[PDB]
Image (cartoon, rainbow, N blue to C red; front, side, top):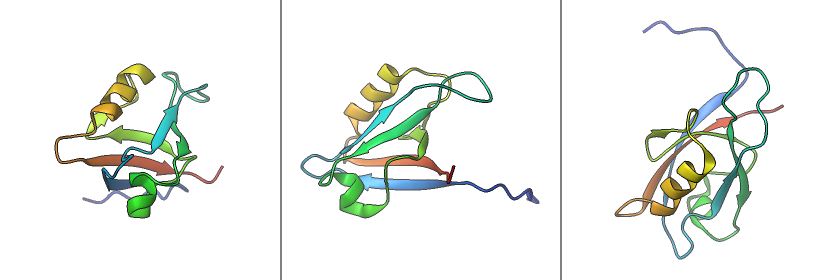
Length: 101
């Protein structure tokens, strides 16, 4: 469809495969500016887990969804347990928003 607006920021669909410490990325939520719900951000990227293993994820980006579940609307504890579950084979779908703020 014709969707054309051009915003400086993009979302990335990233699948990461569980290694030894597969989900080596952790999230945080602080404050929301413009809106209201508190955004989920990737805080830390462990130098040895799936993030580096596939090398697609980094810290700083806003996490939009993980494993196909929407974050904006749920709390960290809900997202963390969603993260801790990983998936059965171990491939996690992260959607991040790359922002250069």
